[PDB]
Amino acid sequence: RDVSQDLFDQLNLFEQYSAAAYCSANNEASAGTAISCSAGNCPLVQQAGATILYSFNNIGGDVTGFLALDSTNQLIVLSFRGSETLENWIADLADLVDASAICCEAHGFLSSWNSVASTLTSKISSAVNEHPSYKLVFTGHSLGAALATLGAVSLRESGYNIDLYNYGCPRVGNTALADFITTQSGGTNYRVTHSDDPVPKLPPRSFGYSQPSPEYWITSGNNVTVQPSDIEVIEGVDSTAGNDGTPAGLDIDAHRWYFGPISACS
Image (cartoon, rainbow, N blue to C red; front, side, top):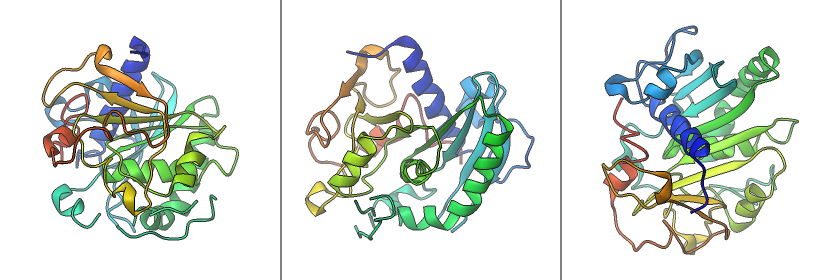
């Protein structure tokens, strides 16, 4: 209802970034190589001239993705990849840890993050000292999506202006953490959901988990081209509308589809 064309194109661009995080060619690639996607999984960034600044594969959980520069759109993107074995990853997905360093407490996710955190923050600082006029964006899909969200909420403690673009992100922490992510003056947050996606539903909210807002929920089905008319914004934090309002189930093909097959390049 309330979404523009250029913002829709930005959402598609960052979902294609998250999809390029799946390409094994873009992972562990030598710095300086351009971003390429098998089966045109990301032609909007592949034709945007994004250069790989760093590519990481298996560090810490399975932290995999790339930090890249985009001078056509003038921004530095840190995109995390989900899980190579996503169906084995959704099975053991519900422990909670004490994450009062941001507080209120988060979920494995923060484990892998704080494992890669010092090195990735050093590289991010170098990249943003390179181009101080570029926007810092963290993004990802599924597991990586979580690694993106926390990955931002732990770097806004410093004077970092970070925009977040998660696709099919699970729940990371309590309701206080959702409120903190919702109310933060260090950049805007774009949480994207799609249909009967069981990944934003898990871990269950009964067990203390909660997801922040706004929720950008697309009404399009699986394996179907999407239009901005199908995208609705949801304002209530931890709202039973959109994805969380969809009934229980395991529509994994709905999690496979986010503006295109986001997980099909590994």
